[PDB]
Length: 184
Ligand code: MNH
Image 1 (cartoon, rainbow, N blue to C red):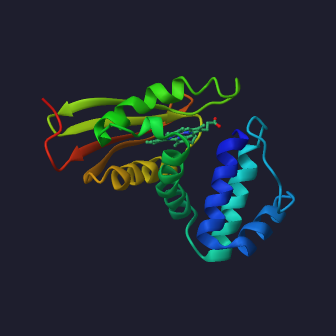
Image 2 (image 1 turned 60 degrees about the vertical axis):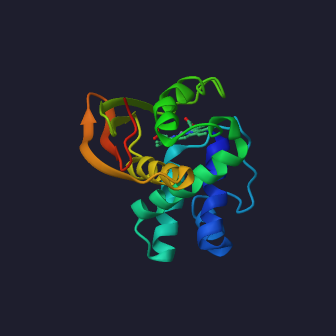
């Protein structure tokens, strides 16, 4: 992972569970508890994993629900730092453009690998979206979808169609249905 997002995860976790919990968690992996992560710094993925794990044991909160809450909260942050992505759009446009964003974000650092998020209409009021990654950040993905729905103030139902590994890649396909009719 690259530092920019990792740092974002760390701030959010503090915002949610307090500094004590975060710092000791940060200490448990051998980081300085006040570490300053640089945008293009290479942060080991497993190190993040254990930080979240440690937070889970310190709050008694299931680690997958922590990841979902981090996701929910990240949309707000993203809207503040990249408002050009949110302005003049309805939820459906945002979600469908997300794949493009990531493909054109792989430029941020040359080593960045954010997942595919290919979306496609499957009805007048529904789209499929498929998360595809070498990682398995299923709840982070689902959290971000829910947070997008809250931000745009458009209700959705999210139905999970497929989950699991398929040739080297972890995948999660959901069917996203809009209450109000979105397409013609
Ligand atoms: C603006 C909006 C926006 C931005 C700037 C954005 C940018 C990023 C960046 C940068 C990374 C880190 C990539 C890396 O390799 O270090 C990342 C990771 C990620 N992103 Mn997106 N992201 C979304 C919205 C955004 N994401 C939305 C919406 C979703 C889901 C619907 C999403 C799903 C993810 C997931 C899940 C990861 C975790 C990496 C992975 O799963 O492989 N996201």
